[PDB]
Image (cartoon, rainbow, N blue to C red; front, side):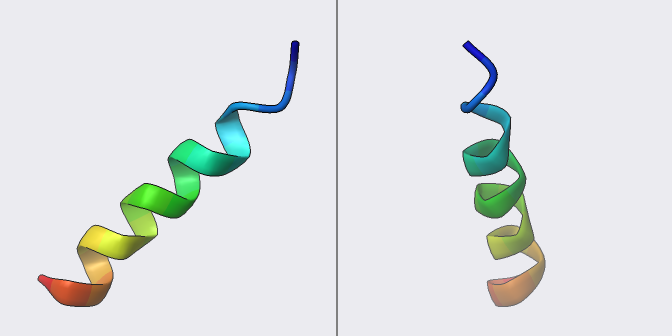
Length: 19
């Protein structure tokens, strides 16, 4: 089911947020 990629991208954008 296509609906798990939207979460992955978000998590990453977090790495760029803190670090």
